[PDB]
Image: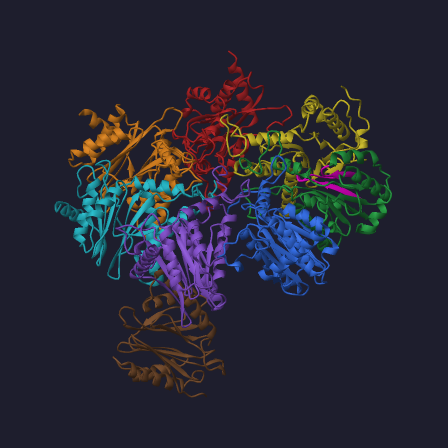
Chain colours: A brown, B orange, C green, D red, E cyan, F purple, G yellow, H blue
């Protein structure tokens, strides 16, 4: 019941040569909303993003410690991390606390450097990676997101179709969840640009 | 630098000399020769034999307790050359390492791996200045299921290697030359031929006729992988079969 | 030169080198005189002011261990600070545990137990690397009446009727030997201590040049003020 | 030339001189002998008395390591007492772990390894004593071992450690101890101790005797006073020619 | 018995600003057997000589060219047991990196970690620096790598270099013989020629140890391949 | 044990620390590192001691290390000790970023590393780090900054400074030629080229013997870049042309 | 030389010089005499003062109800050993509810004092003890040394000029056993007097007596309780 | 785990490491502190100015709290460590006692730390001397000086570092109640004391000034030049009148 304490929902989707990541913007404690612009998606590279759902304090702690490790990695190696290596690093960070686990389920979306191949994955609270080829979801409304994505997702979607699919899935999934919503932010990561959009959503 | 150059404390602790030498390790090698005995190990086509000379200067001493042959496991045997207490400590360490290997990995340690572990411990001794390297030499004997008989020797310097034939002690140079001569004319060796080669090498480098009470022989064979020490009857039979020819 | 031997090596005569060197270092300190009479114990120490710009009130060569015990030190004062802190802590701990005041001998013993607790090997980091270079004079009043004790870096502590420590201890001890008698009063003890201090001090004795303290039955540890000191030194 | 100050230093000729100096310290102590007969082991110590003020039996050089193990020492007595404590601890731990009395060979090996552990480092000093371990049991028979300051342990039929060990060994070599019983061996040990003692060099001494064997049901103990008096009178009568 | 090691540095600064223990370890390295490493267009070749003082030694028992991972190799010049310790530590470091990141360690990262270990033994108390210099080859992202790590803990990226006895002459020979766009076979031939420049006696398939690293990974050449290459010269 | 100890962290009869002075001698033996602070940036110029025909291409820089997004450093002395110190610097910067979610100011990082150096020089019985460092960076409190650290643990801010081989001559040249308050990036680069030309007398000035990195601010972000070989070649050509024109006019 | 600064260094003659220097430290101390009868053990110690105005240094200490000690040498080491023995006695009475046997306490003292003589950076305890105790075996007199060697003595004297006291004890050791308490104390006082200078004589200031027995717990007589023992002594034989 | 006894006694009865630390202090720049009636002034000489050094990062005078500041002479890094420890101590004391430290309290803490480093295994004493100055809660000015041996005394005026003997003699000959009547007189006295040891007529001089219940104030070079001009005018007037 700790994971539902703050709510939240994060979704990542694969396109033909692009990835999309989306999250809700509500920060709240139990049934009370506090702010409507909480950040759950954090850049981890030029074309690499991580979405964190769960305890907001653990979201921030994991994001900051991951930034620590990633900065040290990129200073040591002189290169940018690959999404699979970032997934492994997040798994190691989460499994280090195996008996004191952080209450966050990370979602990673990005393009592989030097290949620009889309990559999406999700992890459990102790660091079990799940690399899929269509979509990964996390948060308090996983069933609604699963229904929406299984119904709407299609292979080899262009960035416009990918945006429409992920936005409809996120909007209709969070419209059916009490402790999620109050805005949706979507990042579309192409090989040459990154587009950030905020969706017109319900505020109840 | 200079051939005999020394600076600071390089003659007292294991720090580098101006030429990059470690004098304490060489002094441990001389401590090996301080013992006064010589042992010879010979590898056959299907057996491995270790022969060392037994010294019982006084009759009051119990001869059954004066041994340089030790068994590490059921299938590995060793001969020790050098300081007796150092040799016994190294034998205890080798037995512990073999038992721990069997406990941890579920199968008996190979001879090469045991020699490598002992050499690693001796290297750790050679790199730290707080302690003294052991003045002893270990020759390991065993049968490997793939390679067959194995003869491995480790030294105080942390160096180990496998051998077709090897020697350690006061007369190891003459024994090495004799074994070189006997191995260059390589004719396939049986168990009897291996035992004869080892015994005659020791006898000729000591230039004496041997009695069954003056030597100690341990063997491993492919037929009987267990390490066993020959009794005085078998050593006497080998000595007679050597002396007739 | 000083590192060829450890801090805990015996001399061929059976003496620790470091302890003897600490005893030698004591002789560089200022003279402190303690007199134990039947009416109390008086302590007097030469301040040894070096510059007129140095405030004499910032020199504490007599300290209050407890309301009934005082301490006079000679040698290395910074070394004596930790010993004084230990003495005060021991007195407070004894009061906490037993609801009573310590005897002077027990305090002196507790302080003296720290003297030889030094060494290099088989010791925790931060332990003393050398003996303390300060001699202490403990003067207090307990159920045995007024009492004066002397402690030295070797750890030995003895009860003294009258003693002097410091650079001019040899000369002052002889003077203390002649003047001291068992039936001496506190006024006579203070006057004799001041006379001997004036005799042994290089600088002319005045109110700011010296520290004087007394402990009496029923009276707490009292440090003489400037006016009281000027009253005492009026006749000398 | 600086090669003899630490046990962690070899000489250019491959010797550890601190261990040899500990051996020299052992060589200056009074002689203690031990003879293993066909059914037991008998110890004998020439206990020099340095003052008439000391009580009889003071500074005993015979020890009980276990119920069945006896210890005879020579050299620094404090080091010998520490080693006796180590041997007692080893025997007690062996009984606690494996549930039976420790064999003498295993105990000798353990204590010899403990002794050898002090010959490797500059932070410690090699032991300045050598000692003999004797025991008897029905399964194992009579066993006698000796450990030197270097840590070398050997089994013996007759051993001697101390000031006069060559002469004591010569006296022991004349004994057919392999065919003798403990009762004769006590008298022989007393005679040897009286022979090797130097009246002029050492003014007075006490004869310390102990044994372990089937006569004591495999328990090490001090020889009874009647046997001790008989052995002493035999030795004194044999000394005069 | 005491386990207290010395807690003070055995390597200190000389009045001229030198660390003479490092220089003595370098002298120990320079007295070692020759070692040659050449970086070609499609791979790296590590070549070294292993001549036994007697025929009684078993050639196949102990190796001087060692694999660290499936893509990283190692050869040395200096003291063998020190090399064994460094090989064990390098393998452990590579396995730790693979455990953390689930990808094979890049050659440069492993070189940096081994150099850090060597620096630790250069500065930490109660120990002496290693008496070995390491030649490390690797293949990452379709790119060959060749590094040399010295006893002081410093590393250098190389195209071709030599260690051990007569390494200055070997360096000059490589300088006049090495050129870019070289293939792996030509690099192997050049390394064998560099070894022969200082070799005394007759060089056979068991006198030298050769290891190659390319896209397929790192592996030690079997004595048959070495014999064929020697016959090719 | 007490006889093999060298007493690295003890005073001298003159009140000196000998090991620190010997480490400073080691610093003097090292390559020349130069740092100049301008109005619109700050640069590092280093002499590449790793010159050889068979040496492979360096990845980013031989002696210039990026510490974080806003700082870079250059080292002179023992290379492996410099690696240790740079790793510690990166760790300290990332720890500050984790604790405050803001980039660390430059002087705090220099102070932390100098505290580590002093701790080594005071206790522990270990030899000191034989590395001197030059720091360039930008922060929101003081803007562009240039610091220098010594093996003794001392540090200080400079407008222009030089460490390593021929440091005194370069310092005198900077005193003569540096115009405080009027330097730009181009003027600072020309001054650095001239100073390296006079200091590196043994070797003619070529782009392969010199490492130059600059730190600028562009649209509220810090840019740390190393000049390409063609840029350094053009700078050397410009300096040579200026030398020729000055010779001809005189 | 190079063999006299560390206790972990043997000399080529087979000796450790630091231990001998600690024994010299013991020899520097003031004389104390211990002797026993069939029923009592008595320690008499000649105390010394730094000056005429200084009280004489304590020489006899309480360990348990049945054990008392007299010291010679470094007083800090003596206090350390005395605290250790007090802890051992308290632990014995806590665990087994019986007084600790004297011989076992002396064995513990020897075991404790042997350790510093074999470890680098440590020093021997520069103090020698005379231990008087009573247990199931009767009175006991024990002497400990910095060499960690202890002796069971019929009588003993340690400190400065103790040879004359030891000679007197050797002379009267035959008479000691059958003496009563007063005769034993007078014998000990005469032995202690044998170590005094020609001009110096025994008095109530410089003499302390420690007595233990079957029905008598360990007691120390310091200033005015000494006089009944001192009275009755004869003139110095000279 | 280095446990060597660095500071040990000597046959003469001396601690050689502490004496060498004092010698290291004797090589530092001169620091002068004077306790006025309502002001306290600290002045530190600069041994060399390179015209390229950033003056902000080489300030030898620092504030320990809002009411206590100190100046030092000796080794700059050791002084930095001591200053950081003193600042942490001041903050912790304000935490646990709910009141700002007195000058004597922080002086005691610093002296105790130095004494600890003079008697603990595996370390050498701090080679610095400090001039701790400030104001009590009652408002009394306080000036203290510490030394590597761990001893501290209160002063009316003092000088540490190189050439400290001459400055101390000048202060003894010049410290009077008529010389500290105003803040200007105290500042001029500090500058005059520093001027004999220093050269260039006040260019290599740093001044810091602390008043009651006021933050520490560093003097810019223009104010120092003005005070030097005032001192020169006074000296020339006295010379032209008396002689």
Total marks shown come to 0
The image quarter in which residue H39 lies: bottom right
The relative height of residue D136 versus residue E218 in the rendered view (above or below) is: above
Residue H75 at what x, y percent from top left?
55, 50
Decide which of B150, F91 is in the foreground and name it: F91
The relative height of residue G91 versus residue E182 in the rendered view (above or below) is: above
Residue G16 at what x, y percent from top left?
54, 30
Residue A189 at what x, y percent from top left?
32, 76
- Residue C159 belongs to the span the image colors magenta: yes
- Residue B45 belongs to the span the image colors magenta: no
Decide which of D136, A86 is in the foreground and name it: A86
Decide which of G51, D28 is in the foreground and name it: G51
Q: Residue furthest left?
A: E232
Left or right of F24? Residue B195 is: left
Looking at the rendered image, the quarter that the C terminus of chain G falls into is top right
Tell me which segment is drawn in magenta.
Answer: C146-167
Residue E56 at what x, y percent from top left?
22, 36
Left or right of F202? Residue D233 is: right
Question: Can residue G69 be seen in this snapshot?
Answer: yes
């Amino acid at each position: 019941s700790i994971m539902s304490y703050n709510g939240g929902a994060v979704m990542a989707m694969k396109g033909k040569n692009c990835v999309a990541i989306a999250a809700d913007r509500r920060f709240g404690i139990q049934a009370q909303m506090v702010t409507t612009d909480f950040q759950k998606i954090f850049p981890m590279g030029d074309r690499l993003y991580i979405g964190l759902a769960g305890l907001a304090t653990d979201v921030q702690t994991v994001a900051q410690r991951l930034k620590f490790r990633l900065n040290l990695y990129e200073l040591k190696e002189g290169r940018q991390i690959k999404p699979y290596t970032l997934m492994s690093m997040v798994a190691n960070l989460l499994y280090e606390k195996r008996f004191g686990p952080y209450y966050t389920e990370p979602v990673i979306a990005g393009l592989d450097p030097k290949t620009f191949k889309p990559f999406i994955c999700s992890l459990d609270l102790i660091g079990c990676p799940m690399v899929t080829d269509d979509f990964v979801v996390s948060g308090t409304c996983t069933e609604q997101m699963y229904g929406m994505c299984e119904s709407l997702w299609e292979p080899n979607m262009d960035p416009e179709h990918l945006f429409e699919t992920i936005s409809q899935a996120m909007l209709n999934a969070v419209d059916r969840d009490a402790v999620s919503g109050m805005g949706v932010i979507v990042h579309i990561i192409e090989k040459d640009k990154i587009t950030t959009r905020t969706l017109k959503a319900r505020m109840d | 630098m200079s051939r005999g150059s020394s600076a600071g404390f390089d003659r007292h602790i294991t720090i580098f000399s101006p030429e990059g030498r470690l004098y304490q390790v060489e002094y441990a090698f001389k401590a090996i020769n301080q013992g006064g005995l010589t042992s010879v190990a010979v590898r056959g086509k299907d057996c491995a034999v270790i022969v060392t000379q037994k010294k019982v200067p006084d009759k009051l001493l119990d001869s059954s307790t004066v041994t340089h042959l030790f068994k590490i496991t059921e299938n590995i045997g060793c001969v020790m050359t050098g300081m007796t207490a150092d040799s016994r400590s190294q034998v205890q360490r080798a037995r512990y390492e073999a038992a721990n290997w069997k406990y941890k990995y579920g199968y008996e340690i190979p001879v090469d791996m045991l020699c490598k572990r002992i050499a690693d411990i001796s290297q750790v001794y050679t790199q730290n200045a707080e302690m003294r390297p052991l003045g002893c030499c270990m020759i390991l004997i065993g049968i490997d299921e793939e390679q067959g008989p194995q003869v491995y020797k480790c030294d105080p310097a942390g160096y180990y290697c496998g051998f077709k034939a090897t020697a350690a002690g006061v007369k190891q140079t003459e024994s090495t030359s004799f074994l070189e001569k006997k191995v260059k004319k390589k004719f396939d060796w049986t168990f009897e031929q291996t035992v004869e080669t080892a015994i005659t090498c020791l006898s000729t480098v000591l230039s004496i006729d041997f009695k069954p009470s003056e030597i100690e022989v341990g063997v491993v064979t492919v037929e009987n992988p267990k390490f066993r020490i020959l009794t005085e009857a078998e050593i006497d039979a080998h000595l007679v079969a050597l002396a007739e020819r | 030169s000083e590192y060829d031997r450890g801090v805990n090596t015996f001399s061929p005569e059976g003496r620790l080198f470091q302890v003897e060197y600490a005893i030698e270092a004591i002789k560089l300190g200022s003279t402190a005189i303690g007199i134990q009479t039947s009416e109390g114990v008086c302590l007097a120490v030469e301040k040894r002011i070096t510059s007129p710009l140095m405030e004499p009130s910032s020199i504490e060569k007599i300290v209050e261990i407890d309301a009934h015990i005082g301490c006079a030190m000679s040698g290395l004062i910074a070394d004596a600070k930790t010993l004084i802190d230990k003495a005060r802590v021991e007195t407070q701990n004894h009061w906490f545990t037993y609801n009573e005041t310590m005897t002077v001998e027990s305090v002196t013993q507790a302080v003296s137990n720290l003297a030889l607790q030094f060494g290099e090997e088989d010791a925790d980091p931060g332990a003393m690397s050398r003996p303390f270079g300060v001699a202490l004079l403990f003067g207090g009043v307990d159920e045995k009446g007024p009492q004066l004790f002397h402690m030295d870096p070797s750890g030995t502590f003895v009860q003294c009727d009258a003693r002097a420590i410091g650079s001019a201890s040899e000369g002052a001890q002889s003077s203390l030997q002649e003047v001291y008698h068992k039936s001496m009063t506190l006024k006579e003890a203070i006057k004799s201590s001041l006379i001997i201090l004036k005799q042994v001090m290089e600088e002319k004795l005045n109110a700011t040049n010296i520290e004087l303290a007394t402990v009496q039955p029923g009276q707490n540890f009292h440090m003489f003020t400037k006016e009281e000191l000027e009253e005492v030194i009026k006749d000398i | 030339t600086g090669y003899d100050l630490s046990a962690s230093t070899f000489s250019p000729d491959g010797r550890v001189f601190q261990v040899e100096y500990a051996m020299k310290a052992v060589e200056n102590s009074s002689t203690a002998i031990g003879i293993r007969c066909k059914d037991g082991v008998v110890f004998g110590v020439e206990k020099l008395v340095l003052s008439k003020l000391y009580e009889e039996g003071s500074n005993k050089r015979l020890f009980n390591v276990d119920r069945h193990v006896g210890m005879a020492v020579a050299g620094l007595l404090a080091d010998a007492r520490s080693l006796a404590d180590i041997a007692r601890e080893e025997a007690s731990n062996f009984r606690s772990n494996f549930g039976y009395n420790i064999p003498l060979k295993h105990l000798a090996d353990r204590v010899a390894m403990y002794v050898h552990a002090y010959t490797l480092y500059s932070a410690v000093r090699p032991f300045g004593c050598s000692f003999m371990l004797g025991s008897y049991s029905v399964n194992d028979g009579a066993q006698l071992y000796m450990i030197d300051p270097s840590g070398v342990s050997y089994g013996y039929w007759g051993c001697a450690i101390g000031k006069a060990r060559q002469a004591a060994k010569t006296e022991i070599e004349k004994l057919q101890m392999k065919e003798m019983t403990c009762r004769d061996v006590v008298k022989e040990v007393a005679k040897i101790i009286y022979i090797v003692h130097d009246e002029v060099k050492d003014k007075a001494f006490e004869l310390e005797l102990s044994w372990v064997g089937e006569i004591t049901n495999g328990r090490h103990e001090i020889v009874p006073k009647d046997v001790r008096e008989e052995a002493e009178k035999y030795a004194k009568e044999s000394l005069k020619e | 018995m005491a386990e207290r090691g010395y807690s003070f540095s055995l390597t200190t600064f000389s009045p001229s600003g030198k660390l003479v223990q490092i220089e003595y370890a370098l002298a120990a390295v320079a007295g070692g057997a020759p070692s040659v490493g050449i970086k070609a267009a499609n791979g790296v070749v590590l070549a070294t000589e292993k001549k036994q003082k007697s025929i009684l030694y078993d050639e196949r028992s102990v190796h001087k060219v060692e694999p660290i991972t499936k893509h990283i190799g190692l050869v040395y010049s200096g003291m063998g047991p020190d090399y064994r310790v460094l090989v064990h530590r390098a393998r452990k470091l590579a396995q730790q990196y693979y455990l953390v990141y689930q990808e094979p360690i890049p050659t440069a990262q492993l070189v940096q970690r081994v150099a850090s270990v060597m620096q630790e033994y250069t500065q930490s108390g109660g120990v002496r620096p290693f008496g070995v210099s390491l030649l490390i080859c690797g293949w990452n992202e379709g790119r060959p790598y060749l590094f040399q790590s010295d006893p002081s803990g410093a590393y250098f990226a190389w195209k071709a270099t030599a260690m051990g006895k007569n390494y200055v002459n070997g360096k000059t020979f490589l300088e006049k013989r090495y050129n870019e766009d070289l293939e792996l076979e030509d690099a192997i031939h050049t390394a064998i020629l560099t070894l022969k420049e200082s070799f005394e006696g007759q060089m056979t398939e068991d006198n030298i140890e050769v290891g190659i690293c390319n896209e397929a990974g790192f592996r030690r050449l079997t004595p048959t391949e070495v014999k064929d290459y020697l016959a090719a010269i | 044990s007490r006889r093999y100890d060298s007493r690295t962290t003890i005073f001298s009869p003159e009140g000196r620390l000998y090991q620190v002075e010997y480490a400073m001698e080691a610093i003097g033996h090292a390559g020349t590192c130069l740092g100049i602070l301008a109005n619109d940036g700050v640069l590092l110029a280093a002499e590449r001691r790793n010159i050889h025909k068979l040496l492979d291409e360096v990845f980013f820089s031989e002696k210039i290390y990026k510490l974080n997004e806003d700082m870079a450093c250059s080292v002179a002395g023992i290379t492996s000790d410099a690696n240790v110190l740079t790793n510690e610097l990166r760790l300290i910067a990332q720890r500050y970023l984790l604790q405050y979610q803001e980039p660390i100011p430059c002087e705090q990082l220099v102070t932390a590393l100098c505290d580590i150096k002093q701790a080594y020089t005071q206790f522990g019985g270990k030899r000191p780090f034989g590395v001197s460092l030059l720091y360039i960076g930008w922060d929101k409190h003081y803007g562009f900054q240039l610091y220098q650290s010594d093996p003794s643990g001392n540090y200080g801010g400079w407008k222009a400074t030089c460490i390593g081989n021929n440091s005194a001559a370069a310092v005198s040249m900077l005193k003569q030629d540096y115009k405080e308050g009027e330097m730009t990036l181009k003027s600072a680069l020309a001054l650095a080229i001239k100073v390296l030309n006079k200091t590196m007398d043994v070797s003619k000035l070529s782009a392969e013997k010199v490492e130059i990195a600059t730190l600028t601010r562009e649209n509220g972000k810090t840019v740390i870049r190393v000049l390409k070989q063609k840029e350094v070649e053009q700078l050397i050509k410009k300096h040579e042309e200026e030398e020729a024109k000055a010779e001809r006019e005189k | 030389n190079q063999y006299d600064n560390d206790v972990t260094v043997w000399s080529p003659q087979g000796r450790i010089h630091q231990i001998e220097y600690a024994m010299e430290a013991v020899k520097q101390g003031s004389a104390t005499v211990g002797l026993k009868s069939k029923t009592h053990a008595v320690l008499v110690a000649l105390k010394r003062a730094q000056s005429e105005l200084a009280a004489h240094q304590k020489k006899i200490l309480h360990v348990d109800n049945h054990i008392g000690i007299s010291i010679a040498g470094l007083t800090a080491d003596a206090r350390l050993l005395c605290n250790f023995m007090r802890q051992e006695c308290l632990d014995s009475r806590f665990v087994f509810d019986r007084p600790l046997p004297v011989s076992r306490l002396v064995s513990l003292i020897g075991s404790k004092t042997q350790i510093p003589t074999q470890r680098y950076g440590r020093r021997p305890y520069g103090v020698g003890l005379l231990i008087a105790g009573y247990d199931d075996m009767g009175p006991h007199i024990f002497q400990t040394c910095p060499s960690a060697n202890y002796f069971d003595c019929r009588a003993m004297s340690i400190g400065a000029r103790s040879q004359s006291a030891r000679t007197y004890l050797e002379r009267h050791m035959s008479e000691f056993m059958e003496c009563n308490l007063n005769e034993l104390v007078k014998h000990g006082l005469r032995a202690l007097r044998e170590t005094l200078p020609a001009e110096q004589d025994l008095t109530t200031k410089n003499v302390s007596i420690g007595i233990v027995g079957k029905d008598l717990e360990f007691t120390i007589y310091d200033d005015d309780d000494v006089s009944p023992f001192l009275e009755g002594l004869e003139e110095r034989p000279q | 785990s280095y446990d060597r006894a660095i500071t040990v006694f000597s046959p003469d009865g001396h601690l050689f490491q502490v004496e060498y630390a004092q010698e290291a202090v004797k090589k530092g720049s001169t620091a002068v502190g004077v306790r006025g009636k309502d002001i306290v002034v600290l002045g530190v000489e600069k041994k060399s100015v390179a015209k390229l050094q950033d003056e902000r990062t080489v300030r030898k005078i620092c504030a320990l709290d809002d009411n206590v500041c100190m100046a030092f002479a000796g080794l700059t890094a050791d002084a930095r460590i001591v200053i950081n420890r003193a600042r942490v101590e001041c903050q912790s004391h304000r935490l646990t006692v709910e009141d700002p430290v007195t000058v004597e309290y922080i002086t005691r803490y610093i002296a105790s730390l130095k004494q600890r480093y003079t008697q603990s295994n595996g370390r050498r004493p701090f080679g610095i001397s400090a001039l701790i100055v400030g104001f009590d809660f009652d408002g009394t000015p306080r000036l203290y000086q510490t030394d590597p041996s761990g001893t501290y005394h209160a002063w009316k005026a003092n000088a540490i570092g190189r050439g400290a003997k001459s400055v101390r003699e000048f202060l003894e000959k010049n410290y009077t109640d008529e010389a500290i009547e105003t803040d200007d007189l105290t500042i001029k006295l500090v500058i005059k004391a520093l001027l004999e040891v220093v050269q260039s007529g006040g260019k290599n001089i740093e001044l810091a000034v602390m008043r009651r219940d006021q933050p520490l104030k560093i003097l810019n070079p223009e104010e120092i030049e003005k005070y030097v001009a005032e001192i020169e005018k006074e000296k020339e007037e006295n010379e032209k009148k008396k002689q």
